[PDB]
Image (tube, coloured by chain):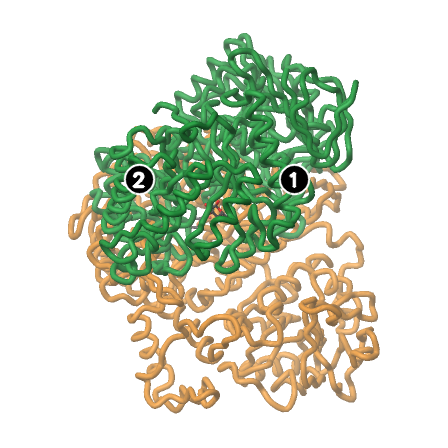
Chain colours: A green, B orange
């Protein structure tokens, strides 16, 4: 599927896009001149329109009014502001759900999901599909021929709320998905191990989705659950593809996207898979408060880039300050608004947008920050948004557009499907999920001055000097071979606990762990040692001999190969059986290359262990112990021009080596002759 | 009923049974010769088969095939391995629930319980009874005279998930049980105090089970709830009785059992009552991780013996290492495999089995340990299993079989009905339940080198030298006469807070606590003093004058009798009204015998207080301050042979006086001329 990036309005140059969700249909019409006036002053040059506007467009069944939308598009176009137009199909009107309550999502207990919030429709309902596909057709027909429209924003965050449906529509389509993937019922029975607890299937007609099995102390089929999660993603991908085929047929030159929600902990949609279906990848991401703020945002933006295969990507939403949807919504500290935007940009984005333009006075999102606060033009956030628009204009003129996130020395593998598998309630421990571990390695390498590339499992991590395999619970035979081949030919691999436990069907590998690849890794494990404080006197941590500490889970390593070296061992009470067992090992395999980390060390423990592990593998690290003070993010043009961003990672002002080049952008920082200065949350960009 | 013990295969001697749930229907057929081979090598002499095999026996309605099952039974019989055969009725096929969804269990809130796990049937559903009782006939008809079958494993773990059903079948059957228990509606009104909040019943037709009352802040009738729990247990007991009757009719000489879930915390089925319905008692028990590991398993096994009235019993399931069903599933430490089995064996088991033979690759229980792990015969678990089989063969040859768990000096009373009663949500505090107290008493006497016998309340505790009455919340007049008579004639009693609060209908006794027994105990209490940290500045503990601390709840002892002595008082801020009040008293009554403990002490508090209490009661305790280091469990033959087992209770290697006689078994232990050595988790057995 070819990359096609939204293009300028007629007579404008190519620029970093900079905008917001705009919702003028929630204000009186006469607010729009001020909006536009402030958007111009802020250097805003695109808005996303009509995302949730279904009910103000098809105002009653069969009745489509476009006037208010055409008027504001006109006003925006005359001002030089492009329009990312939504399909308007995110959330249906009251008249549609009143009249057809059968579009309503059902939860795992059979609860109806009422109107009164959003995205409360069943992804596989035919009635709902027909309405959507009609609105799509009407929107497209009305706006082909309209030159303000530069891209389609199809739907909105599919499966954010409606990922899991259990309606009879879902019952039916999950069967058909099973028939299509498995052909014959006996193939389904093998994939799921239905000979456990009299679950054996006679026919496809017998397959149900994992509805309520009584809650706690009751365990649903794990392979079925995996496939169900797969199916839920596919069902909405299918729905999205249909909406987009309809818009594209009528407006073939108009590039189409939908907004992803890629973040460290996202555990529903398989975005890498959806990525084959969009003309350019776009993402919505909101900061994690506290210490994780910087590293988890960088990690995420890197993964977007990975999912993107290094094509430029579109930041469709983030917050200027507080969000509204956590138990506690911290505000952003000074400089974090410009800094976070620059982090997404540094990680390859060529568009930077917010939810949303103007703060609502009312509705569930009234407390969600915006580009123009209820406090108005004379506010810190608006001033900062203006400074940010100028910075992006400056970076547009410096020629940053279309440069790629340069290729890191290390790839960190991310794998939603391994994440699904690790969510079963009957694993060795609920305290391990796949998603935390790749983030831990990303931060630890950053701590040692290394910017890793986060890559989905199907991307080309096997072309990097090095790869991290973190809790990659699912290993197929083709994955085994890819990994084997990689290390054979000179690859360095860091491989952790919880990797290669099962095949792609969640069928646990036999004869010892890691499954399939024990030859490459040169380690053998018969069982896990989970850790915690569930009951008094439980073994709750395991010290490691280099001064670190494992929590949640260690591997019990039974034996290692003759040419495996032990870098570190566990230190425990002798009654545990863990004392003196191998905790960190290194093992050659032809021209590589394999380190094994036999429990959860956390960002800090990985970081402590990195020098020793890398030395033994041949992977070179900056000797500077200031290495972790700053995150260094580099985009490259094919023509040779290099853009390097620096971010302070820490809670004090730091000083660092000035890179070569022209200083382009600076927030809470200072350029000098030898040394660059960065305040907390400061950032610099250089071209060289 | 008559004790019948499963008998050897033709031409075999009697041996301790040693085996597992075996699940050949989950594996390809050609795997069996390997199973049988490794079984022989491990000394396994029995397996339990077809427990969840409905779907592969009645493969469609009325269609019964037995081929695969006769095949494996033949391989096993050839290899000298007996079969404990299931009714196969534990969990119905997908075709049966497809066609008759009215079998599905209904929860407290009316949700359907779907297939996809197990035991999702209504205990009183007449349709499901029909199906089950036919499958029973077919199994019995097909296997009568087949000499490999040495026992029936009827259903599985009744009430493990389906204990509480709220379907119309349960509605209708609860009325019937009430009509049969009370005769007239006025007696129902009397037992449950329905004149509170306009609940008085006009007829049995108005009797409903305790469905949802709106949750938090709403409180269901506690007398009704009590009887409802009794009913849920009787309703499943009856189902079992019917299944079993259909089986012993066809096969009058094959002894039958069903697997109980006796453990310190279980709080559903009344196992002592069900024990009347089996030919021999069998139990599934899984370790508590941490400090509680040893004491809670010995407690539970002791209770099985008590429930068994000291007849030999059958450990039907336990884990070689980790289970799969806690949020954190720790593995067993080295030696705990053999030690735990020896603990069950020491407490009176003549048969030791695991769930399960071979670790599943798939299904909800794939992470549950087995005798033969995924990692294969080359694994520590399988090696330890082999050692254990040799050990149980050794003990077989020593003549342990049918030795009885010796009579302790103190019985500790357990009482499922009191447990039920203490579960209501409007008691003085939710941090008091009956079940923790007898366990605390077991562990404490053990710390003072006394192995108590845990006895259900209807067993003969009134024939021990001492009894512990721990939170026996329900006290009928007959129970009070039993305790009075026991103490009159020279008994020694330890009686705690939360005893004799209410009659057998949960109707609180009047005129002061403990009710009925105030004369025997010598203490009068008007109200409780609950303790905890729910609001700032709440009274959260009360120190006691012998240096212990009470938590969660204390009595307010208002007055003691003329001849009651105070051994210890509460110490507290004077404003509490608790400072100087009686905390532990002792009171003679004719030739006995009564100590009263007015609050929750913990294992440590009881342990610290035992010497002063036992000295004052005249109960002799070992003078050795090392007494708590090892747990001594003792089985006896009529011919006077004696099997003494010794277990290290502690987390350090311990040393102790060598027992007289022949060393039989050692694990993580060591023999010597004067002293015996036990490592943490060690065990030794001797015969004399
Ligand atoms: O932070 C809240 C924000 O989240 C995403 O960006 C949605 O697509 C927005 O419309 C809004 O709900
Ligand atoms: O610990 C899990 C295990 O527990 C009990 O023994 C059940 O009867 C088994 O069938 C199995 O589910």
Circle 1 is placed at which residue position? A336
Residue plotted at (34% across, 64% down): B106
Q: Nearer the viewer, residue B485 or B70?
A: B70
The answer to whether residue B652 of the structure is visible from this angle is: yes
The answer to whether residue B153 of the structure is visible from this angle is: no
With B573 as the anchor, is A381 left or right in this view? left
Circle 2 is placed at which residue position? A143
With A403 as the anchor, is B206 left or right in this view? left
Which of the image's four quarters has the C terminus of chain A?
top right
- Could you give the CA–CA distance between mark 2 and mark 1, rounded to whole angstroms? 38 Å
Viewer-nearest of labels 2 and 1? 2
Look at the numbered discs 2 and 1 and tell me whether their residues touch, using CB distance below 8 Å.
Answer: no
Describe the element under mark 2 as helix, strand or loop.
helix
Q: Position of residue B36 (x, y in %)?
A: 37, 32
Which of the image's four quarters has the N terminus of chain A?
top left
Check the residue under mark 1 and report the chain it is in: A
Describe the element under mark 1 as helix, strand or loop.
helix
With A1 as the anchor, is A288 left or right in this view? right
Badge 1: residue crowd in 10 Å (few <14, some 14–19, many ≥20): many
Q: Considering only vertical position in the picture, is B85 above or below B376?
A: below
Badge 2: residue crowd in 10 Å (few <14, some 14–19, many ≥20): some
The residue at label 2 has a CB less than 8 Å from ligand 1? no
Q: Position of residue A257 (x, y in %)?
A: 38, 35
Give the image quarter of residue A2: top left
User: Upstream in the sequence, badge 2 or badge 1?
Assistant: 2
Q: Considering only vertical position in the picture, is A455 above or below A373?
A: above
Check the residue under mark 2 and report the chain it is in: A
The residue at label 1 has a CB less than 8 Å from ligand 1? no
């Amino acid at each position: 599927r070819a990359h096609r990036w939204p293009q300028p309005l007629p007579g404008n140059d190519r620029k970093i896009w900079f905008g917001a969700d705009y919702n003028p249909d929630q204000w009186p019409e006469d607010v729009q001149d001020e909006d536009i006036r402030l958007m111009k002053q802020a250097g805003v040059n695109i808005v996303s329109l009509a995302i949730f506007s279904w009910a103000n467009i098809e105002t009653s069944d069969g009745n489509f009014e476009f006037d208010w939308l055409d008027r504001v598009i006109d006003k925006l176009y005359k001002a030089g502001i492009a329009v990312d137009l939504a399909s308007a199909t995110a959330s249906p009107p009251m008249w549609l759900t009143s009249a057809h309550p059968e579009v309503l999502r059902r939860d795992e207990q059979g609860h109806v999901i009422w109107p009164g919030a959003r995205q409360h429709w069943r992804p596989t309902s035919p009635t709902f599909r027909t309405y959507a596909l009609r609105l799509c057709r009407e929107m497209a027909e009305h706006y082909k021929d309209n030159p303000a429209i530069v891209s389609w924003h199809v739907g909105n965050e599919y499966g954010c709320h409606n990922y899991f449906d259990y309606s009879d529509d879902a019952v039916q389509a999950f069967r058909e998905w099973c028939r299509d993937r498995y052909g014959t019922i006996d193939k389904v029975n093998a994939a799921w191990g239905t000979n456990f607890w009299s679950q054996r299937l006679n026919s496809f007609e017998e397959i149900l989705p994992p509805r309520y099995v009584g809650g706690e102390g009751n365990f649903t089929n794990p392979g079925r659950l995996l496939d169900f999660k797969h199916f839920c993603s596919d069902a909405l991908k299918e729905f999205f593809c249909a909406e987009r085929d309809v818009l594209s047929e009528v407006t073939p030159n108009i590039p189409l996207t939908t907004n992803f929600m890629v973040s460290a902990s996202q555990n529903t949609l398989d975005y890498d898979d959806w990525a084959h279906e969009v003309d350019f990848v776009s993402n919505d991401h909101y900061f994690t408060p506290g210490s994780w703020h910087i590293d988890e945002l960088a990690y995420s933006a890197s993964l977007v880039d990975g999912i993107s295969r290094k094509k430029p990507w579109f930041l469709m939403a983030q917050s200027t300050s507080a969000v509204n949807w956590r138990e506690i919504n911290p505000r952003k500290e000074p400089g974090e608004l410009i800094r976070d935007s620059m982090l997404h940009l540094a990680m390859g984005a060529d568009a930077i947008c917010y939810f949303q333009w103007r703060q609502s006075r009312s509705g569930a999102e009234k407390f969600h920050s915006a580009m123009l606060p209820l406090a108005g033009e004379h506010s810190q956030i608006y001033r900062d948004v203006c400074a940010l628009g100028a910075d992006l204009d400056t970076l547009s003129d410096a020629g940053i557009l279309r440069s790629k996130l340069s290729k890191a020395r290390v790839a960190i593998v991310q794998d939603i499907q391994s994440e699904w598998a690790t969510e079963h309630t009957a694993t060795p421990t609920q305290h391990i999920r796949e998603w935390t571990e790749p983030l831990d390695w990303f931060a630890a390498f950053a701590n040692r001055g290394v910017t890793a590339d986060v890559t989905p499992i199907h991307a080309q991590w096997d072309t990097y000097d090095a790869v991290v395999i973190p809790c990659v619970y699912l290993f197929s035979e083709e994955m085994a071979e890819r990994l084997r081949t990689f290390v054979r030919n000179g690859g360095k691999a860091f491989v952790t606990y919880y990797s290669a436990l099962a095949d792609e069907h969640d069928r646990l590998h036999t004869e010892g762990w890691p499954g399939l690849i024990g030859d490459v890794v040169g380690v053998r494990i018969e069982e896990h040692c989970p850790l915690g404080t569930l009951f008094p006197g439980m073994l709750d941590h395991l010290d490691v001999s280099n001064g670190t500490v494992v929590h949640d889970l260690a591997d019990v390593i039974d034996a290692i190969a003759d040419d495996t070296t032990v870098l570190a061992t566990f230190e425990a009470d002798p009654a545990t059986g863990m004392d003196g067992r191998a905790a960190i090992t290194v093992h050659p395999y032809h021209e590589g290359g394999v380190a094994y980390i036999a429990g959860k060390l956390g960002r800090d423990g990985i970081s402590q262990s990195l020098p020793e592990i890398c030395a033994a593998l041949g992977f070179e690290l900056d000797a500077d112990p200031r290495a972790g003070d700053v995150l260094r993010v580099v985009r490259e043009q094919e023509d040779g021009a290099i853009f390097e961003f620096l971010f302070n990672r820490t809670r004090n002002t730091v000083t660092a080596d000035r890179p070569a080049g022209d200083m382009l952008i600076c927030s809470l920082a200072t350029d000098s002759t030898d040394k660059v200065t960065l305040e907390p949350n400061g950032v610099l960009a250089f071209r060289r």
